[PDB]
Length: 77
Length: 378
Length: 56
Length: 48
Image (cartoon, rainbow over all chains, first blue to last red; front, side, top):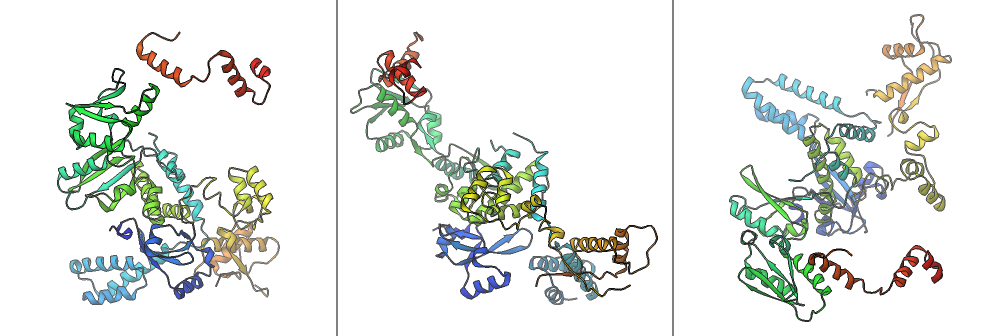
């Protein structure tokens, strides 16, 4: 089958662990509601098998910095 | 100086990873040409670090306002008006998050089995392209003696469509069960089963001619172009989900003009990337140089909540937490009354509300805090 | 540690405001200059007493 | 009152059978009065 992550427009998506999520929240001094949101019906979310309440680490292909890290919180539809 | 020493110095230097690789490659290229010494390499690395530190943006900069100005100013010299209609209408449609863009265009790529020869590309295109009965027919004539509509088609368009006559009559007979279809020569003859009223003939004649014989819905025109010793298929209309699962089509590089289809099929991050690419392509076509950082900031603000949002009263401004900022932009009475109903509280953390009241804005010098020891003497 | 343009502007404005309503100049200045010019000269001499509080 | 060419006449007949609900002028006047002035007596709607 055609994986959703093989597209050039789709960056790598990885589910953060609990300790990784806590460290990310501590680093930026933000709550879980101050992160960008991603819908639970997103193709990347259903491909990763994530559930609402998790934080997805996105490895963007930066035109300026080469590789850039973005974080999105899974929320219900 | 060996390459290992240069790599070690580059790694020891404080630089981003993308800068480190480019600097190492340039130093390797220049090392054989001019026989660089260790002190020269160290000075080059120090200068690169200093330039990187100098290029860092200072805190407190109004990046959003600068981005909005740097996007809106080149639009004042844009040009208005195959069938791609770029320019100011295109960027307006992009920033307004239009559900259905005007003249959608789908860029379709092919795998290794079809990207080398024109015949495979042509048959893939004819598989993608949607052909119905009304375009195949030469003229329309309602016949009353048989009490049913009669269809005739030219041989050239039937041959180029890729399906023969038997395929056509099997397509309509399976799809439509109210009336039967008979064919002789190069003509279609339709015969009713329980149709007697003349008014019921028109409702069944139009349904027959608009039925799609083959291809994907929403695609009516398809062209093929060659670039970089590869064949790229450009279609009119957008059906991303259907065209993704089509044999002979590479789904890794296939993209569409509709950002909403990209979000629904690929993801929100892919939608943001598509928005950035569309804005960059429009600016490049118009001949206007705009820094990509403004475009990525706009796209990040557009896809903050996981869905594509416009920049108007129904998008980013509509979901602003400030009552005064929302009321000041487009809709004043409705927003104020809605805030009065809910008892909303405006924390005055934004810029517009502080401008309205007469308080310093939280940008530039407004975020600077000062302290001073009192026992100060000359 | 280097001053940003916004921080430098805020420091110069605060010093000029202080000079306008008192706060005698800590360095010798030519006669007939504005308080803003005196604050700029003080900043050039590196004698400003105003610091910047940064988040931590 | 429209034309005599059979192509126009076919569309005319189609319109006539599609609009066979109204038989006389009074019913069409009732429709016009209902659209212009809904919720009014029949005489007032007819006059309007």
